[PDB]
Length: 191
Image 1 (cartoon, rainbow, N blue to C red):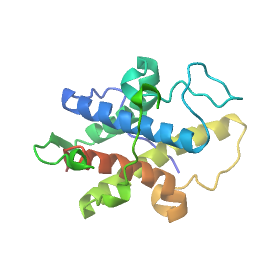
Image 2: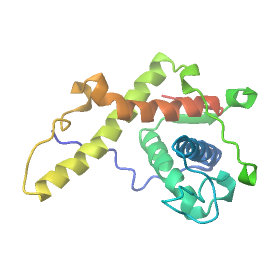
Image 3: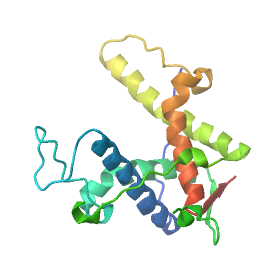
């Protein structure tokens, strides 16, 4: 097993994707904030572990560039892989289905039920390729970690296509999420 992730070191993201990166990063932050809230954290001015106060629980537009980058970075990494593969990416006029969807800083993040969104057979297949690439990224890093600890093995150091569903899940869910968000935000990806 020699995992080689798609090399995206020289990929430039075209301007047409900036809207998406900003919107999906905002969504990712809203998800993070809602998860924090469910775990007993609230917004406040000064961070505290003991009081469970998280100054990051505010609107995405109010975050610093470094704070936004936490969310933008992996999204950009995912998009660069699509771009490296030459996948066609187009904004559409009528495809932004999320538009129709029915506290400090007035912040009220809402969940999106992604299980309401369906991917075509071809898009599911493209998501599987993305998932496999996420696995290869992890696997290459793990293979290097082990080699540098003197050796050893790992049950997940096999090709993605030989993993079971439970083992595929983390990477599959990440891949399906970006494709679903592309769809509902008005982008059409094809090959």
